[PDB]
Amino acid sequence: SQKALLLELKGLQEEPVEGFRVTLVDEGDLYNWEVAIFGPPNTYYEGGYFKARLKFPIDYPYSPPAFRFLTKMWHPNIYETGDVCISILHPPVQNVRTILLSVISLLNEPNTFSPANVDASVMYRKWKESKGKDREYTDIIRKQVLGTKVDAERDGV
C-alpha cells in the first residue's frame, strides 16, 4: 500500500535511526527510496558517508523490498552490484526501521555462513585468525571510507 509506505516514511522522518537519513527519490513515487548512511563513530566506517537504495513491491508489506548499495562496498555479505539479500537484513525472529538496524549490525560484524563476496570473506577471516595483525580487510574499508568524502562534497555534511 501507498498508505503503508506513507506511514513508514513519515514514521522514519519523525523518529530517525541515528546515522540514517531516508528520503524519496522522486517525491511522486513512494516505491523507490534513497538512504544516506553515516558510518558509526568507533568502527572502521567512522567518518564515512554511504548511499543505498530501497525498492518496494506494489503489494508491500506482503512482499519485502530490495536493498542495494550505490557506494561500492568490500564486504562478505554485499554483492559487487551493491545488493544485499533481504533475508539477512530482515532476519527470522516497522519493517524498514529493522532493515536499517541490520545495516549497522552487518557493517559491524559480517556473516560468513554463505557469503556474497568470498574474497572479502576469506580476507575478513584472516583478520580474525590473526588478532587484527593482517590489516588488509581493514585497509580497504578505510580507503572506501575516505573515498566517500568525494561523494560528500558532491552533496555534503
Image: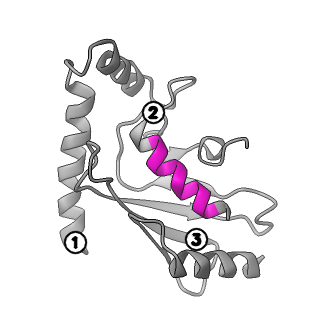
The amino acid type found where label 2 is placed reads Pro
Residue 82 in view of the camera? no
Q: CA distance from mark 2 to mark 1?
A: 29 Å
- Callout 2: helix, strand or loop? loop
Q: Residues within 10 Å of mark 3 (few under 14, many from 20)?
A: some
Return the x and y of residue 67 as percentages of the image width and height.
56, 54
The residue stretch that appears in magenta: 96-106
Question: Which residue position holds label 2?
Answer: 110
Farthest bottom residue in view: 28
What residue is shown at x 61% (from left), y 63% (from top)? Answer: 96
Q: Amino acid at mark 3?
A: Asn
> Percent x, y for residue 62?
82, 60
Sequence-first tag of 1 and 3: 3
Q: Which residue is mark 3?
A: 32
Q: Secondary structure at mark 3?
A: strand
Find out whether residue 101 is within the magenta segment.
yes
Decide if residue 69 is in sight here.
yes
**Label 1 to label 3: alpha-carbon separation:** 21 Å
Percent from the top left, x then y, of residue 98? 60, 56
Q: Main secondary structure of the magenta part?
A: helix
The numbered mark at residue 154 is 1
| Colour setup of the view | one colour
Q: Please, is residue 44 above or below residue 110 in the view?
A: below
* Position above or below: 79 against 136: below
In the structure shown, which secondary structural element does the residue marked by tag 1 occupy? helix
Judged by depth in the image, the label closer to the viewer, 2 or 1, is 2
Residue type at mark 1 is Arg
Q: Compare marks 2 and 3 and give the one earlier in the sequence.
A: 3
